[PDB]
Image (tube, coloured by chain):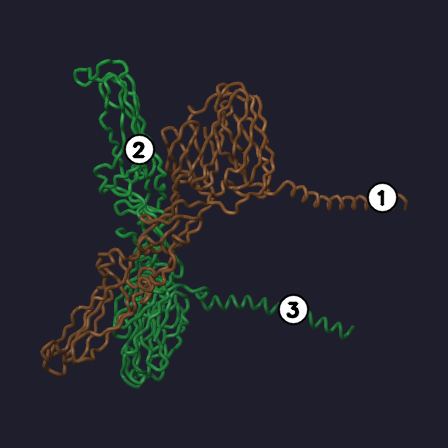
Chain colours: A green, B brown
Amino acid sequence: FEHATTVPNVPGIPYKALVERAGYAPLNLEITVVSSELTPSTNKEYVTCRFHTVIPSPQVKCCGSLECKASSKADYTCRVFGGVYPFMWGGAQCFCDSENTQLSEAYVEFAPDCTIDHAVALKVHTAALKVGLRIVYGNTTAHLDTFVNGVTPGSSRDLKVIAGPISAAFSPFDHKVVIRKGLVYNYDFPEYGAMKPGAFGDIQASSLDATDIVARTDIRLLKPSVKNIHVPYTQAVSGYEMWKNNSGRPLQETAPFGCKIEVEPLRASNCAYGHIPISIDIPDAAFVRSSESPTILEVSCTVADCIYSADFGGSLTLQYKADREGHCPVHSHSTTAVLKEATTHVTAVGSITLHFSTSSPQANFIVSLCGKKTTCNAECKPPADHIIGEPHKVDQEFQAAVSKTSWNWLLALFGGASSLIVVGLIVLVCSSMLINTRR
Amino acid sequence: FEHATTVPNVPGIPYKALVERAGYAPLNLEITVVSSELTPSTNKEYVTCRFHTVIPSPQVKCCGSLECKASSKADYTCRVFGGVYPFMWGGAQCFCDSENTQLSEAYVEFAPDCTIDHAVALKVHTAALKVGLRIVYGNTTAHLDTFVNGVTPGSSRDLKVIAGPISAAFSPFDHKVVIRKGLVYNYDFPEYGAMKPGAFGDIQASSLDATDIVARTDIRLLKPSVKNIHVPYTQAVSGYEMWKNNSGRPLQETAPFGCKIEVEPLRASNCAYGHIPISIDIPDAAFVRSSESPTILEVSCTVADCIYSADFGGSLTLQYKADREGHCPVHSHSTTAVLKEATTHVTAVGSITLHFSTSSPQANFIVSLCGKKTTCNAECKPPADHIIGEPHKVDQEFQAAVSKTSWNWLLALFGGASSLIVVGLIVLVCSSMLINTRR
């Protein structure tokens, strides 16, 4: 027996259903999304951090002439200066003081502490949703993990479940993401090679230990002026530090739909949105024919005080006549009414107290016990409490929250105009026909 | 001095231009796409190969009953059977002829040869193009590698180039790709976990040696039926072999635009399509004032026999009168004409014979020598050969790819009708005027 439902993607909130086989007793089913993991596919564009600007020791030709040779270091910069005549401790490191060419060399690398403090740039793609699910049918329960795509099945030893696709796809991540010490930022970054001094990614590499480090930090050498040997230079501030100062709040604190952004691997956990269509192939052994479970004769519903709060703020009683002691499942067949309990011991003759939650000001919902139904009609007051730390267990339906008094008044006011226009038309027709007869 | 051009993305075919700063002599710029690789953003989803069906040794509880457990191994399959009464070599392996419960266990792993003979399933997205470009300006030639996106720059010691964005976006790879031994296939494969037995991807894993292998080979065990011990079983045929047999042609032999597909990393080299905009800031040292380069007093053009084709089949002669001996650049500003030479020696007065190629039936193209123009008009016949092993160096237009004789005939036959209609309107107006005046 294959049963298909549309379970709301709301972790921690059970969904109750009643499989109603044609020739067998109905069986209870409860569906609990224990966990969900929306994980995208990531590729490491590069890793950036506070660059260490390393300046190799300057070299001086005595009074000959040096030349700048091209290298492959990150933002390699080299310059030639004329007569310098450097001083160290005696004060003359070079003879022939004129034409005293000096070479100034500088480049950048990764700082020693970058092994931990570093930002990884990623491009995220279409994200697949995986849900951990607990299903309990009748007396037997099972745990499983499935992929929400509509093709990937889940198998638990008798149970075959097909989940998905999601009704409305959503990915909190933009096209491009940055990861720093577990903090996620949806901040666009320059592409590989497209580097900008003073901005994020002002030093890029494929790995911390990778030797193909590429840098463009806008470093320029300056002519030395003091007698003592030293190479001056100027350089733009670390754009990584600038981004860190102006990083903004991480995605953990601004991801919509209230869900935890985790790393290693990048993913979003317990993240409620839309619905999942799930089809379960219940094993035939679970069912039992209606001749075994007692079938009640007649049942009546008396609704107690009801409040359409976010919790089980309603109660009712079911008075039943039956043939034998049993364990009937109890269900609510309305979309704006849920029940705390799914099954109950049932005697031959008696009554049972039940609890329920709703969201409309009116209750007009169908309860059912060992298959057979009964309407319950009631008026519910607004909830006394303003705020609860518990999510709403149902959703108010389109124009189903209109109370009986409001319905009566609105229908009366519209029907007044409707009656007025029809009597106007019949009066007009009567006058026209009267004139035609007496014309 | 920034000069912007639209270089056609065609490897091996030079693009020639003339930069004309107002107060300085013109300079010749040859721009040659030596190499160009388009690499997409890639991420490994899983690998697959022909499963090795590993079937552990059976166990018999010799006078009792066992229970099958559960494990996380790839496609863990286990079954329990009743009395078996197995034989080894002697004639007996259990007493208790009844109640000889047996356990059959089986699963799948990667075959030892899968370390090389395996397929990798990838998901690709928008691809950035990288161009290796040789630029010759004046008397200086330089080589560069850059990303054609309009922001990523390139620099060669005085040259400063910004290329992109590509005019037309194109990637020869569909959203899902497969790689096997360097052969690239544009195949749609099952998603991670969306595993169908008997087809490609029947086994998946994130790495060859990973222990978290997921597998679904549709393995079903049978009750042993012979006296001797064994574990009968049937299994779906390896879908990897089925895809190998029905792999079709690889993407190397189907990629359009003649794009050579290479692996490690996956990319397409020498992929000619569209045009790339390039802005080059030429160093000020190359330019020279007009007073130094010999300005030519005048020029006359005489075009010899020509055929519009890909090769340099057309020829012309320039009679030049000048004042000093120099090295003028020669250019064609027409879109449908290119020159073999870009810099030619010039004397006080003389003749120079040049070669050129075009694509129009008639050459109506303007040549320029040290900035001074000449509208070369000619009449090119269709070529002799049908097929050349050399690409066309000029695009085919519509406003110019029509013979002047056909232009004249078409215009005459279309203007005859216009003349007829205007004389018709004139005679109608004359008749109206005559009947109005004479009424």
The amino acid beneath tag 2 is Asp
The circle drawn on residue B29 is none
Q: Which secondary structure, mark 1?
A: helix
Res. B247 image quadrant: bottom left
Q: CA distance from mark 3 to mark 1?
A: 65 Å
Within 10 angstroms of label 1, few (less than 14), some, or many (20 or more) residues? few
Is residue B226 visible from the viewing direction of this image? yes
Is residue A310 visible from the viewing direction of this image? no
Task: Report the residue marked by disc 3.
Answer: A424
Residue B65 lies, in percent from the top left, at: 14, 77
- Dot placed on the residue nearer the N-terminal end, 2 or 3: 2
Residue A372 lies, in percent from the top left, at: 37, 79
Res. A47 image quadrant: top left
Query: Position of B212 compared to A362: left or right?
Result: left
Within 10 angstroms of label 3, few (less than 14), some, or many (20 or more) residues? few
The amino acid beneath tag 1 is Met
Are discs 1 and 2 located on one and the same chain?
no
* Residue nearest the viewer, comparing A347 with A246: A246
